[PDB]
Length: 466
Ligand SMILES: *C(=O)[C@@H](NC(=O)Cc1cccs1)[C@@H]1N=C(C(=O)O)CCS1
Ligand SMILES: [Mg+2]
Ligand SMILES: [Mg+2]
Image 1 (cartoon, protein in one colour):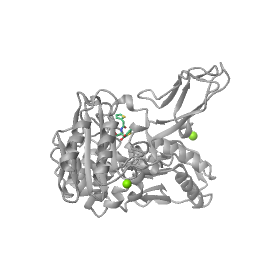
Image 2: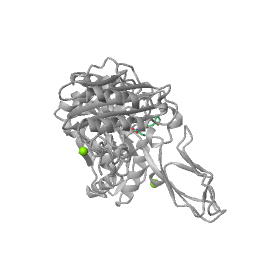
Image 3: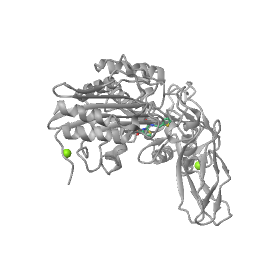
Image 4: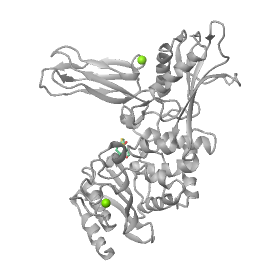
């Protein structure tokens, strides 16, 4: 058994896919508390998205699994006669789930409260958080994609997965030689557009390219899409999430009989109206719930918003520095020795982050005993599970093995970095394990991971399906 499992893991770690790579692998039994396996457990390594474990085990400590984020609209004073108001501020406070409709339900309320004309400018206020959009060491080349969307307190979230600070761009073919049709999704009318994409012959090489050149708010498209090609869509971030939530809400009011004479812009409530009238409000779901679409798909923008949210709680400052300090200590009050830790962000996107397989495992145990241990274990990706909201980043891994429907682990992928940490619940023992790989030069060593996971699934007393 134990004397056996060792040789197995060792052999799996001898995979050529890991040459030159440093691997942090640690396995412990959450019950007995016995150390089943350990190789370089103390080595500091980049955790990539596995950093989200620390971020989630802290948000639940700081904000409570019942936490809810709210949004609001306000004017100095309510309307009356011709139901006319001056300036209006869209004020949000870190809701990571603001839907387009959520804004439309508020556009309606604004009208349902008598307003019929906004003779003033339409400002968007997101001061609950600082205006520091990206972590200092993130790379600017990664700024056009959903993974690296700017952080703001007031940002619109796309789809059922809540991809924040982004817009869905679409490219539809035409006739060979004619320009292609580009729709900018929500950022239509907001972000600029430079359509250089043509429609290529039917059966031609698709060479489409959707970009947001650094430093601008322009969605650029180049290359060509074949005439016979199927319509393409793609998430893209926008400069200043708030200004877009501002643009959409402006469109939303207009869709609810409220005319806006002034301009739409970035601004905070004057701090001159200590008792402004709150024309409408919105409350999101509880963190316990938002947890799911966070840890299953590793929402990066969610992670950072939580961090800062922790920074507003523990110290009234929507900031990373304050947020991270909160996480560090919250992980300490949770009983986690945070010595080998180095927190530079909440998502794991930063190469300034560092953990040790032991610190990860440590965190796994402690979190299992917290009064929120269930809403936490359930947020984790389940192996081999076909349904996106259950399998998450593990929906296409370990299908048909003892690990199917069993392993609850968190992933982490980055250039030269990959990780898998979680629990393997088996009648033969509750298990917590961490696998961190840094330095390999080829693709993520999934098979190596899966192999160890699936072997643990067995060690825990599971069998592969027939
Ligand atoms: C976590 O690692 C995070 N990864 C990325 O955003 C990839 C980038 C690293 C630098 C710039 S982009 C999320 N987690 C994934 C996982 O498998 O855990 C995959 C992508 S998004
Ligand atoms: Mg528009
Ligand atoms: Mg089973």
